[PDB]
Image: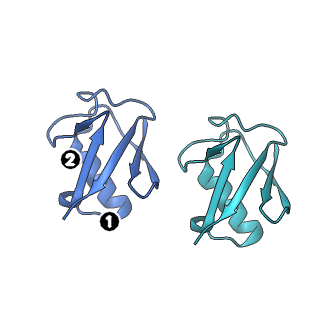
Chain colours: A blue, B cyan
Amino acid sequence: MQIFVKTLTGKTITLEVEPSDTIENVKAKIQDKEGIPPDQQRLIFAGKQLEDGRTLSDYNIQKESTLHLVLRL
Amino acid sequence: MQIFVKTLTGKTITLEVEPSDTIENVKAKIQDKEGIPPDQQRLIFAGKQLEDGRTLSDYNIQKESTLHLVLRL
């Protein structure tokens, strides 16, 4: 399924993911696509800070859901 | 299908597109036709700022629809 990751800059990037993907998997995919280290990534869906060991299905992330990416040092 | 892209200068350019084209696809076509880098392009349809990962069908873009192109640095 495709999901959208939207940055505070307004840029959106598309990722092809599985419901069984974890948040770690998604950060590693953002690392591969955009070069952002996972430790510098904060992901948010539907008002929740996404925690590492849980899956997209756990958070009810679905086709063309938009997640928010906030960068942090 | 043909769509029209109208600039603030009044110039209109014609693009042959598919409903499955994404906004990224359209900006790459404008890049090819007019040499404008995709990062300098802002596309607007029917009052909405067009976001990258979505398709023309998503936005109800249709035959001979007019989009608006605003350039940005």
Q: Chain of mark 2?
A: A
Helix, strand or loop at label 1? It is: loop
Q: Residues within 10 Å of mark 1 (few under 14, many from 20)?
A: few
Q: Residues within 10 Å of mark 2 (few under 14, many from 20)?
A: some
Q: Residue at x 34, y 35 (%)?
A: A18
Q: Is residue A20 above or below residue A31?
A: above
Q: Residue at x 22, y 34 (%)?
A: A55
Which quadrant, please, contains the N terminus of chain A?
top left
Q: Is residue A45 above or below residue B3?
A: above
Q: Is residue A20 above or below residue B15?
A: above
Q: Amino acid at mark 2?
A: Glu
Q: Is residue A69 above or below residue A65?
A: below
Q: Is residue A25 left or right of residue B57?
A: left
**N-term mark: 1 or 2:** 2
Extreme residue toward the left, this view = A53
Q: What percent of the width, then of the height, locates residue B35?
A: 71, 73
Helix, strand or loop at label 2? It is: helix
Which quadrant, please, contains the C terminus of chain A?
bottom left
Q: Amino acid at mark 1?
A: Gly
Q: Is residue B26 left or right of residue A24?
A: right
Label 1, on which residue? Answer: A35
Picture quadrant where residue A41 is located: bottom left
Picture quadrant where residue A39 is located: bottom left
Label 2, on which residue? Answer: A24
